[PDB]
Amino acid sequence: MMANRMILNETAWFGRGAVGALTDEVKRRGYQKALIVTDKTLVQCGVVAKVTDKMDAAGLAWAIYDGVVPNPTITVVKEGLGVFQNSGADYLIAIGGGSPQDTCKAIGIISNNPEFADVRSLEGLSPTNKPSVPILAIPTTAGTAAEVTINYVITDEEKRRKFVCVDPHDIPQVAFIDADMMDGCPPALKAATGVDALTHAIEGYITRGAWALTDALHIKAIEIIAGALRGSVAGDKDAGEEMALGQYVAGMGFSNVGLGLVHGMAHPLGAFYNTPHGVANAILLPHVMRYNADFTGEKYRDIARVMGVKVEGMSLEEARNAAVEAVFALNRDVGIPPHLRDVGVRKEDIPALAQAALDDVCTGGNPREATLEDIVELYHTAWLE
Amino acid sequence: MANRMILNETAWFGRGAVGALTDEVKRRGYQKALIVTDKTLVQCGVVAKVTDKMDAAGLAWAIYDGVVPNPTITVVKEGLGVFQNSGADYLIAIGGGSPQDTCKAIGIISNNPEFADVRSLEGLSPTNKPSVPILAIPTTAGTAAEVTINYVITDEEKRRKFVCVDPHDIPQVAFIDADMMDGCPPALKAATGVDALTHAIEGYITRGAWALTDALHIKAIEIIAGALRGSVAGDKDAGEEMALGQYVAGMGFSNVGLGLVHGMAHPLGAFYNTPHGVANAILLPHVMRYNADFTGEKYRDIARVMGVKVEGMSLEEARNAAVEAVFALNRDVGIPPHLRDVGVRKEDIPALAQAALDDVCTGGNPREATLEDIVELYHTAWLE
Ligand SMILES: NC(=O)c1ccc[n+]([C@@H]2O[C@H](COP(=O)([O-])OP(=O)(O)OC[C@H]3O[C@@H](n4cnc5c(N)ncnc54)[C@H](O)[C@@H]3O)[C@@H](O)[C@H]2O)c1
Ligand SMILES: NC(=O)c1ccc[n+]([C@@H]2O[C@H](COP(=O)([O-])OP(=O)(O)OC[C@H]3O[C@@H](n4cnc5c(N)ncnc54)[C@H](O)[C@@H]3O)[C@@H](O)[C@H]2O)c1
Ligand SMILES: [Cl-]
Ligand SMILES: [Cl-]
Ligand SMILES: [Cl-]
Ligand SMILES: [Cl-]
Ligand SMILES: [Zn+2]
Ligand SMILES: [Zn+2]
């Protein structure tokens, strides 16, 4: 029926050493001065200087905003926007995971669309008339794929909720997908962000708006990620490079079609508790998959198959169970906590979390139409055994 | 050498103890508080438990809510400026160890301005004046920071936690009220409760231990081991027991010291911003095993009050049983088993171990640790 749109990065560089392309890209574009948007951890760890050392050798000017925090808030966006406005910069370089990537998008959008100074009013299909300030995006987790999506997610601390901004105008001009930038994640962070990448690919494979091209991207991403994540957590170089590619491929799909109830149930955790996005999604994933199983056609057979299960001869019910179990197994293998209680959730908040999840935009993509009671029940199931 | 005890001159205990605050303020003649706290406690309504009572009583207050876990030199300086501009004449610390310690730093520097750099307070701070008076209200069970003479600040430039020790920082009044603590999520109850256990076990076996602190610590171990599972489960009376036990532990350890658990946790906090309670909880049983031969009969006592039938056990057996009872508690309340699980990197172990070797807490440890012993302990705790 309806035609399907795809927004993608016009330019992207892939592989260990891809950040070495940045200075030429800047020179080709004629930009005069960057604002780097990042967090203090990435500065302390030397990750930012991997980029600035190259800029300095090429004679390219920059300034830094390093105030991003996980689950970046309206306060963070306003602070970074002020730094941008006083910096003399003409473009942005986002160095970090989803939290810096998203902050950078917000800054770049508001700078060219000042009617959105309050930040909150960007939620939804932001009616921006101008493209963002140009962004060069450098992910350091594997990851959110925020370098390739048209979305960014802000935490409204005053309202205790996360909100999603969807806007073609925010797409980065160039993405640099370089596992050298990602290797310093602690193993536990690799694990959570990697199962989050898997969640993007699984939810995107089964989302209501799925179509042929996104299905092809998502099923490839699932195969890459499921084959690489244990090795990446273990520190294998090639597995890290595979994770960097797979996490990105997932975004090429889900940006354009949507996610589901895993992300919808994780957003309130981020808002209520400041839970890390990756861990929250990882813990919820297999429970939501079980819930969705009967509403997914043949797709769990494909998921199980590319996660290593010999599905030949299984009934559809068996293949569905096998897909779920393969996710539980991966979570155990890479040390994801088994229960939400383990990561600071309170049972008393489940009613309110569930209403927030029901209302979350990601939930609308879920292949099964969730009810309040389904979400209450899933939180209890995930909370403790 | 005679042994010194510093304690709170005044303290109120039990559910509802914060109800005593407004009268304590009136009796002391203070004019205006600065509340030192964090944004979570404001959001959760915990601060309002206090400020609503103050408002009813006509008592003035302002808030500094910028404390973060593992408070930094930057936080201390920010809060000090807020204090200096607030018109306050006393401090109310509402929170866990992070706000309690920030509050102590503020109150000390306000009356001892030559320590404006913060770092210069490390060790036996040579302050001439008492802190601005502090009324301390813990909201975790917990650090016992309300009753110790210590506070712990993170130097981000030097990537290290440092301990400031000073009789001048003791709070004037502590209010130990489990109603203030009940909102901790279960996982936070678990980690802060095993941290309280750690304080009591390390204090029991520390080099400076003597009769009075031994009596306090073994009672605290009994209380905490008996209550923690129930408190994590939300039982009301268990929460009140935890509030008391965590404080009794501090009555001891403030005055004698801790050991290598705390010494190995400090660099985690500095390197990774690891929560103090979780770090200590994961390390505790491994360090206990390392220390066992240097602990006399005390692991028999620990095992007994943790519910082990030690009658008939050899000392070796009783020691192993104490270690296992701690492993069991950690499983039972959901403490992660390994440091890798909480974001530690193996590549950092050499540097973590040097930092732990040099940490002040390590000097109280009953076994004299070496660099190589600490490296091995990190590796042992890092993964199965
Ligand atoms: N824009 C989108 O389409 C999109 C999609 C998914 C998620 N998100 C958002 O992304 C955010 C989560 O991002 P995330 O999971 O990448 O984590 P993050 O950016 O919040 O980072 C988490 C932590 O890991 C640290 N870290 C990151 N890279 C590191 C490295 N290389 N070395 C050491 N430490 C490193 C950070 O400093 C931080 O402390 C959430 O707010 C989520 O809502 C956005
Ligand atoms: N002698 C001493 O002064 C002493 C002793 C031990 C530890 N410490 C220090 O204490 C700090 C750790 O303190 P902590 O373990 O109490 O944790 P914390 O104060 O760092 O708080 C941890 C988290 O729990 C939240 N929290 C606290 N109370 C809550 C409540 N009632 N409801 C909901 N959330 C709540 C906080 O907002 C914060 O996000 C460390 O920096 C450590 O070095 C000091
Ligand atoms: Cl998200
Ligand atoms: Cl989230
Ligand atoms: Cl401490
Ligand atoms: Cl610590
Ligand atoms: Zn995600
Ligand atoms: Zn402690």
Image (cartoon, coloured by chain):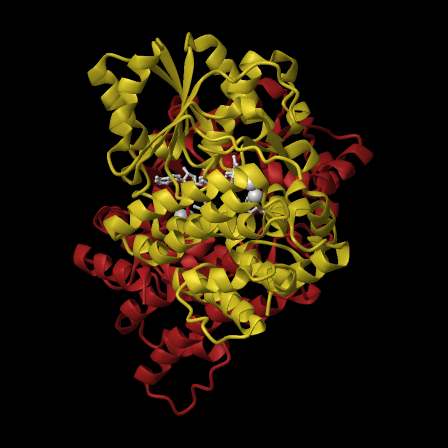
Chain colours: A yellow, B red
Residue A43 seen by the camera = yes
Q: Position of residue B174 (x, y in %)?
A: 61, 47
Q: Position of residue A290 (x, y in %)?
A: 60, 64
Q: Is residue B161 left or right of residue B192?
A: left
Residue at 37% x, 61% y is: B338
Q: Position of residue B119 (x, y in %)?
A: 35, 31
Numbered-mark total? 0
Residue at 57% x, 57% y is: A284
User: Looking at this view, is B159 or A290 the one in front?
Assistant: A290
Furthest residue toward right: B56
Q: Quadrant of the N terminus of chain A?
A: top right
Corner quadrant of residue A256: top right
User: Looking at this view, is B266 or A87 the one in front?
Assistant: A87
Q: Is residue A38 left or right of residue B176?
A: left
Corner quadrant of residue B321: bottom left
Q: Quadrant of the C terminus of chain A?
A: bottom right
Furthest residue toward bottom: B312
User: Looking at this view, is B237 or A299 the one in front?
Assistant: A299
Corner quadrant of residue A44: top left
Residue at 70% x, 30% y is: B29
Q: Is residue A33 left or right of residue B212?
A: left
Q: Position of residue B270 (x, y in %)?
A: 36, 42
Up/down of A239 relative to B238, above or below: above
Up/down of B315 relative to B78, above or below: below
Residue B151 seen by the camera = no
User: Looking at this view, is A374 or A77 the one in front?
Assistant: A374
Residue at 79% x, 30% y is: B58
